[PDB]
Amino acid sequence: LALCGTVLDHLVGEETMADYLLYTLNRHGLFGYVQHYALASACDQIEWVLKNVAIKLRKTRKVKVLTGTGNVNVIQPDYAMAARDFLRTFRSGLLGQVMLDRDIIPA
Amino acid sequence: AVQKMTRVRVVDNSALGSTPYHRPPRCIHVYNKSGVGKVGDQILLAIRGQKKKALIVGHRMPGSRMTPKFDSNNVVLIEDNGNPVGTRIKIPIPTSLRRREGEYSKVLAIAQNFV
Amino acid sequence: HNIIYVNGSVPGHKNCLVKIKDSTLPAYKDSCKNLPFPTYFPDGDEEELPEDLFDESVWQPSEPSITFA
Amino acid sequence: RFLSPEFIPPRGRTNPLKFKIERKDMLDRRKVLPIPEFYVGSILRVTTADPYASGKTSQFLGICIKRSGNGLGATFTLRNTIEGQGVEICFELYNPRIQEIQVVKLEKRLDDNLLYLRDALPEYSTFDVNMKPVPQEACQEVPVNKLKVKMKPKPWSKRWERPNFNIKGIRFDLALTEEQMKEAQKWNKPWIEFDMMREYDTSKIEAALWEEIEASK
Amino acid sequence: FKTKGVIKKRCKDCYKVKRRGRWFILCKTNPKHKQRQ
Amino acid sequence: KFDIDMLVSLLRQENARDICVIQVPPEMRYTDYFVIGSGTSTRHLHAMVHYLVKMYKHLKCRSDPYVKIEGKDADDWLCVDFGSMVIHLMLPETRETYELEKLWTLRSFDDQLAQIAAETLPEDFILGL
Amino acid sequence: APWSREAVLCLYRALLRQGRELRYTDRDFYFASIRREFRKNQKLENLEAREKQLEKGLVFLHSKLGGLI
Amino acid sequence: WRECFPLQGHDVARWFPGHMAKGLKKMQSSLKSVDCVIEVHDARIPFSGRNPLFQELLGLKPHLLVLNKMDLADLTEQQKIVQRLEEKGLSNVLF
RNA sequence: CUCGUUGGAUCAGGACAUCCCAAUGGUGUAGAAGCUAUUAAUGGUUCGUUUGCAACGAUUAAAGUCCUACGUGAUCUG
Ligand SMILES: [Mg+2]
Ligand SMILES: [Mg+2]
Ligand SMILES: [Mg+2]
Ligand SMILES: [Mg+2]
Ligand SMILES: [Mg+2]
Ligand SMILES: [Mg+2]
Ligand SMILES: [Zn+2]
C-alpha cells in the first residue's frame, strides 16, 4: 500500500520502503533499475544500492554522526534522496511493470 | 539526561544496532517515574522500524563526584527476557551498575572493561 | 569554639541567628534522657570534655583512609 | 611557595572563624595523605577505593583540566580517553577513600582551563594508562607547555572563540576565518580588565596563610 | 449485605434484627442470606 | 562458612552438568571469583539456584546483606551476585552462543572482541570530478 | 605457518598437562574445550592468524590457565 | 541470492485522519442518491490490500470493481486475476 | 415539497453517582486472578503520534464521571 503511494510516505519512511522495492524487484528478477541507474550488474544490499545511486544523482548532505569523542557534523551521501528518487521512478514506470501480489495467483 | 527523541549510541556488538548505518537510534520511552533517564535506567529504543528495549550505561550529563562522565550517550540493547542482545561490550562500562537496584550482572559479565 | 555540626540545610542567611532545640518528632521523644538534663555547667567541672566530640559513624580527620573491605 | 588554591578564602561576609576550622581539619588530613603540587594540565594518577568492590581499589589516569572549590570541598577534574571513549571524573581532594595522588608530569598550560579539549582532536586528550613518571626538578620554575591544539569542525560545546573565555591555547587561525574572529570581538567588553574594584588582593592573606600552614608542618 | 428496599427471609433459619437503626436478616447457616435495609 | 569450596561442593551435590571456576585478579574492580555452571533444564536452574540461595541465608551472612536472584524473567540464564563471588547459570545453548569462558579466560584476546574493531573517526564523503 | 610445529605440539601437550593439575573446575570440560578449539583453529590458518592463535597458549598457559582454578 | 523478507517485529501503520472518518458518514448519508457504486483500486495491488468498509457499507447498491493504473502493472496472467475476483463474486471487472 | 457556539494554555472551586490509595461484607472466595456490594471526597488522577475531535503507541497504583454561562478572551490564543 505504501509502495503504490496510497499512504503518505512520511509515516512509513522512504528508507524502509526503499528496501522493500529491492527485495520485491530482486525476487521478481526484473532488474530494470541497473540499466536506469548505472551501478552494477545486480545487488541485493539496500545500503549498497543507495550509496551508488546518490553518487549518480550527485546528492549529498551534512548529517550529525554520534561518535565516542563527541558529536561531529560530517558530510555524508544523501541516502534520503536516493530512497525518494528511487521510489518516484518505480511509480513512473521507468523500472518496469511489476505484480506485487505475484505470489498469490497460485493461491 | 536521556529523554524522548534523544539520538543515542548503541555501544554493543549486536548486528541489528551495532552496524554503522541508518539514523542514530531515538529514544521513545523512559522506564522511570520521571522522564529523565540516567545510568542504569531502561529505555525503549526505536531501531530500523522496530521497538527494542535498551539499557543506559553512560550519558553526557554531569553526575555525582567520583563518577565517570562520558563524551557521548551510550546505551546497550537488552532483550525482553533481560538477556543482552550483544555478545560483547568493549567500551568501558561504569561499575556503579552493580549496586544500583535492578538486574545488571548480565551486562557486567558481557562488559570486559570497567571504569 | 562552641560549634555544633547540624546535618543538611538550616533556614536563614549566613550569620543569621537561629533557635536550636531538641527535636519534637515522635522517634526523638526520649532522646534527652542520656544528655545533660538541665544543661552542662563547665564551671561545675564534673568532667573535662574533649575539644571535639564525634559520632560513631563519622570518620574523623587524621584517621587511616577508609577502605571498603 | 606553592599555596594550594583551596586555602585562599573567597571574599564575602563569612566570618574567618569558618575558614580556620576547615583549615585545621584539612591540615590534619594532609599529614595522613600528602597532596602533591600540581597545576591544570598536569597528568595525574589517583588511587581510590571502590565501595562496590570488596577490599579492592582502582586507579584512573588523566590530565587535570579544572581546579575548583574552596576549603575541604576542593575538587579537581582529570580527563582521559579509553578505547576511543572520552571520560571525565571530578575528584575530591580530601575524600577519605582516596589512597594516593601521583603527579605523573608536573606542568602548566597556557590556559587556566582545558575544558576546550572536548572540541580538540582526540590525540590532544589521549594519555597512556601505564605511562611512567618523569623526573622533576624542585628547584626550578614549573614547565609551561605552550602547545596550541587543533580543533574539530566548527560546532563546539561552547563558543571558545568568544572573548569572555579568553582562551589562549587554541589554533583559531586553522579553524576560523579572520572575518569570524572580528565578529567575536563585538562581545569584547574591554572595560572589565581596567576596573580597579574587580580585583581581589590576597597578598596579606596569602602571607598570613603560609605562616600558619608552615607552622603546622 | 445488599441494600434493598424490601427485606425478605430466604430460609427458615433466617432471623430478623434491628442494629444501628436499620433492619438486618442474618442467617447462621448461609452468610449469603445476610442483608441490610 | 559460605565460601568457594562449600559453594562448588554444593553444586556437585545438585549435580550441575558443567562447572567452571575462574579466579579474578585484583586489578579488575570486580568479584574475587567468577563461576559458571550449566543446567539440564530450566527447572534444574530454578531448583539449584534457589537451593544455593537458601543455603547462603542459613549459612551465616548475618552481617552481610542478602542476594537477589536474577534471570527469573528469562528461561535460560540465571545469575546470582554474592559480594565476593558471582555465579552465572545458563543452558548449554546459551553458554556456547555467548562464550563467557573465553571472555574471562582471555581478557583482551577473545575472538569476539578481536572481530570488533575500533570505528574510524568519521571522515566526510567528498564527491570528486 | 606457525612459529614452529614443535612449539605447537609442545604448547598443545602443555595444556593437557596443566589440565591434570586442577582443583575446582571440571577436569573433563577443560580437556574438551582445549581439544575442540585446537582441532578447529589450527587446521587452516595464515601467518598472521596462526601467530595470534598460537599466542593464546603463551598468554593463557602463563596466566594460571586463564584464571582456571 | 536473497531470502524471504522477515517481519522482525515490524508494525502496520495508518494515518486515517478525521476527514477520512468524516467522509465516510457522507457516503452513508448520500447512499440514497447513488444509483450504482464504482470501486476503483490500483491494478498493481489487486486484492492484497483493500478497504472492506465500502463493500459492507455500500453493498446495498450495485458495486462494480475497476482496477486503474493498469499501465504501471504487469498483466501476464490477467485472466487468472479475474477468476479470483470472480471467485469473491466480483465477476464484472474492467481494467 | 431543508437546520438549529467552542478546543487549547494559566489557575483551578465544589459535588460523589469512587478511577486509584484506605476500611470491609458476600462469593458459584482452596492458593493465586477476579466478580458483586457497602462505607469513605483524604491526596492523586501521564506523555506523544496521526488532527479534526476521533483513533493510535508506549506507560501508570489509576490514566474517574460530572458542575462552576467553552468554569476562566478588561489573563493569552486556534
Ligand atoms: Mg561557582
Ligand atoms: Mg551543549
Ligand atoms: Mg481543584
Ligand atoms: Mg458513597
Ligand atoms: Mg502536544
Ligand atoms: Mg472575563
Ligand atoms: Zn438464610
Image (cartoon, grey):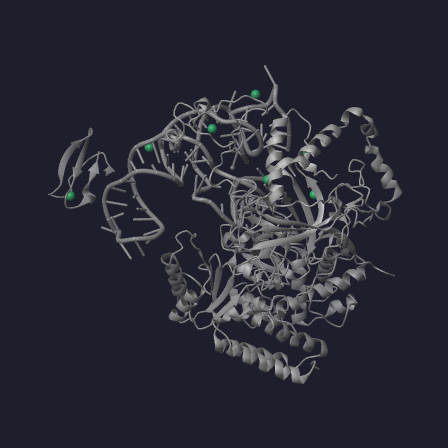
Q: Position of residue F50 (x, y in %)?
A: 39, 61
- Specify whether residue D193 is in view: yes
Q: Position of residue D188 (x, y in %)?
A: 82, 33
Q: Position of residue H38 (x, y in %)?
A: 59, 55
* Residue D50 against residue A18 in the figure, above or below: above
- Give me the residue at 62% from left, 25% from top: D15
* Residue A101 against residue D180 in the figure, above or below: below
B67 vs A52, nearest the viewer: B67
Instruction: Classify residue F5 by image quadrant.
Output: bottom left
* Residue I62 against residue C15 in the figure, above or below: below
- Give me the residue at 81% from left, 50% from top: D150
C26 vs A85, nearest the viewer: C26
B35 vs B49, nearest the viewer: B35
- Specify whether residue B69 is in view: no
- Give me the residue at 52% from left, 46% from top: B32
Q: Quadrant of ligand 2?
A: top right
